[PDB]
Amino acid sequence: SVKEFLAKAKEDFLKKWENPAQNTAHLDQFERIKTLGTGSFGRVMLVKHMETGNHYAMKILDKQKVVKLKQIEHTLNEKRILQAVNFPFLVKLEFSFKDNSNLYMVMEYVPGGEMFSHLRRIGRFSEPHARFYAAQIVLTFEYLHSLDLIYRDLKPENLLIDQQGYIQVTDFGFAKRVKGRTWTLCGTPEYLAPEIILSKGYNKAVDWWALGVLIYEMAAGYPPFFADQPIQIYEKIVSGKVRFPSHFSSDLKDLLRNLLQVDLTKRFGNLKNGVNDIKNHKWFATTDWIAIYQRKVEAPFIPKFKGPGDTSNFDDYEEEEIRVSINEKCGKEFSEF
Amino acid sequence: TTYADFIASGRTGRRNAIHD
Ligand SMILES: c1ccc([C@@H]2CCNC3(CCN(c4ncnc5[nH]cnc45)CC3)C2)cc1
């Protein structure tokens, strides 16, 4: 039973939420191999844990850059939430620690690469391929939302493909535990719900709008609202108009009209029946929700694997030194990390 | 085509999030 499963998941989450794991490793315990990605205030590197020989993805955030970009509370949210969650499609945080200069989050390494890379290369995914990935996001949001968490940054760049072809959601930089409404303007332009652009209070319904954008992008090969500049994207989002490719099935279009819905009293995921309006939609008729959760469904794509520590499924980034200052930076700001 | 318009746009690469 869903209700019973989620109640037990909440008991587990709250114990970790109230007493977060802290300072569980040191930088000297890892061998730095290669950069897997970059952000405005950090980078993610492939590392090898010497004591086990295991490979991990280490996020390194520069404390001073976090402060300049006013991301202190968001970074504390990211680590506090990621250390407390447990779901098959959420990447696991193995260790976390900090030093004079940086914050570090050591997570499972997901070798298949970003959904973004595969989607851009192939062009678009078939409806059954997109449906397989979408079902995993639906279940993941059902789990997160039950814990009063809002994700706020769904996009292919943040969805990694594992060795079994299943999704691993990474990047909890904008996730927040909130019972009421929230107001921060954050996320990625193409994925913003109209209520975020219009500076209204908003809630978990923004994640369901973002799911509509993701499904559209996976099935079309391009997002529903795009332009050269963010301002033009915002005008398209608020207009109340969406065009679908002629190859989209009738069921796919109907599902998307209900997710990409400006009216909050009409948006799927936000009604009296909640997530069940999505799970029971015609486009998901062939989906066995339990088999997806149990990972019993055959994946439509298995990434190529040359062996342990291989990064062939990732783009190459410029390599920079990890400098650790002799003086502690921003100690007070990151005391709880 | 919409595909050709997307490919010729400046937003086919990795998209960064909004910051304050
Ligand atoms: C700050 C620095 C870097 C990122 C990048 C941006 C591009 N997407 C990414 C998503 C995670 N990423 C992982 N790759 C492999 N295994 C993982 N385990 C956890 N995260 C990853 C690849 C790069 C994060 C985000 C914020």
Image: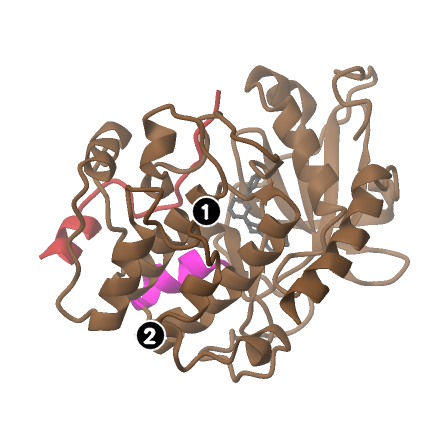
Chain colours: A brown, B red
Span shown in magenta: A113-124
Q: Which residue is mark 1?
A: A207
> Dot 2 falls on which chain?
A
- Left or right of A4 in this view: A169: left
**Residue A261, placed above or below residue A282:** above
| Residue found 23% across the figure and 64% down from its top | A253
Q: Is residue A47 left or right of residue A236?
A: right
Any part of residue A307 in sight:
yes
- The amino acid beneath tag 2 is Lys
By secondary structure, the bulk of the magenta-drawn segment is best described as helix
Residue A313 appears in the rendering: no
In the rendered image, residue A213, in percent from the top left (x then y), is placed at 33, 52
Frontmost residue, A118 versus A150: A150
Q: Work out whether mark 2 precedes mark 1 in sequence or the reverse, and give the earlier one.
A: 1
| Residue A41 located left or right of residue A203 | right
Tell me the number on the disc at residue A126: none
Whether discs 2 and 1 lie on one chain: the answer is yes
Quadrant of the rendered image containing residue A12:
bottom right
Badge 1 element:
helix
